[PDB]
Image (cartoon, rainbow over all chains, first blue to last red; front, side, top):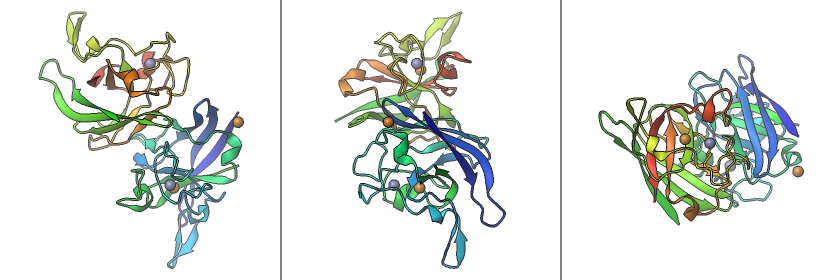
Amino acid sequence: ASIEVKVQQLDPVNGNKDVGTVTITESNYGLVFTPDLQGLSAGLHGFHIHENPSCEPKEKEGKLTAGLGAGGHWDPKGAKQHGYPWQDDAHLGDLPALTVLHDGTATNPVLAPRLKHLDDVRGHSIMIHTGGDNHSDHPAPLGGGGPRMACGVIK
Amino acid sequence: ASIEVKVQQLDPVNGNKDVGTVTITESNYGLVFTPDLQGLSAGLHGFHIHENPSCEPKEKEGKLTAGLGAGGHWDPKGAKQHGYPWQDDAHLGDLPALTVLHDGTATNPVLAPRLKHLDDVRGHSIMIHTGGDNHSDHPAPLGGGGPRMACGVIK
Ligand SMILES: [Cu+]
Ligand SMILES: [Cu+]
Ligand SMILES: [Cu+]
Ligand SMILES: [Zn+2]
Ligand SMILES: [Zn+2]
């Protein structure tokens, strides 16, 4: 059983760019997110499920802003704070951070132990941020993820 | 509760170098390994518990070889194959790979869902390899980790 999610680098001016997939599978310990990506900025990047099945940009403060259509971190249990993948009182969408290798590719899978069934993440989006993720809202909100670099809709 | 493991970059010629710690804690989903490391080569590195509570080098083919005193991947259930952190018929010491950031530091924690109690990993060693970890013995043995870059003894 798997879900293949098509991911794009987001660029409301010059055009979104295909960068590959993230394939979601079930393990005995929770959902596994296996990237097969290329063309992304190298680094450790915040990686979360967001609430809406959208990667569209939205206007904010006069600027068409990448990925805001996805809404916020998926938080169906109302934890109302950002945390660790293994933290029960954190947003359910908080995944382990995504490692983009030096050359822009990403293949290292990560486990979300609080997500147990594929159908639970359908109708949401997966987001890759420009910044990292310290799994806290301190000192920066939402782990320091900042802007939205790439995204896919989980169908 | 936690175990603080001192980690050194291994160099049998010029001398080992202190590179920080890995702190092991218990979560409701298994053991969490939180690095606070510096001075390591940037990249995604294989990260495993090895059998012996040793990081000493050993002679092989006329060469004092870094970290061989630790022995092989910890495999108390006798899986006899390298695999994923969430794979029950893989070596129990198979952890998620460790992300060393571009500047040589490492702070991103990783979860080992098959490890449940701190006492279970006492008396072993934790190893950071020069290569990565594709979580298979194909195409390269032991995930492609290759040589032993840094190590600590879990006590
Ligand atoms: Cu996010
Ligand atoms: Cu299921
Ligand atoms: Cu190893
Ligand atoms: Zn969050
Ligand atoms: Zn192994």
